[PDB]
Length: 212
Image (cartoon, rainbow, N blue to C red; front, top):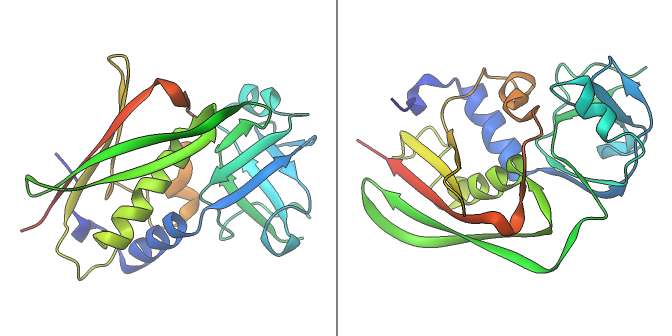
């Protein structure tokens, strides 16, 4: 049972379009301040020179990356982002070690279908050895957002499923209209686990969208 786009508020649609089209991306930064036992602080590295609060699911996760030259790639937001003093910018997970790269860009294909009809195959990449699922998810939704206008209320697409398949019998999927809420601080909690995948172990991506 896939959720219907009609279930989202105009605010939900806007935030979704916005975060999937303008991901926060920063390479080789290091945080060494834990906050609230499960958050990492990167002072002076958010947009506008604001402070960045990277939120994780568990204190363990936060601890695993303190001191780490990490790469960041995720959905950022300001509304309801716990101030660290000044104003602050937030985001969940999307954190990987910077020292782990690939010799060449790993290219992943995404078979696409609208109402069961196959469309042009899409492509996303990453030179990260271990890329977070959030990043892959974002790169796919940006495409689904611009080619199929999934987040425009007046578009014909009303349902959709994104599925990431590994080279082993393991897959991960997202219901593009199943948002925790209408504000990013709730929507993005789906990434707090910081789920990361070995890039070369990913097989392909399946995208099924529907109308009516």
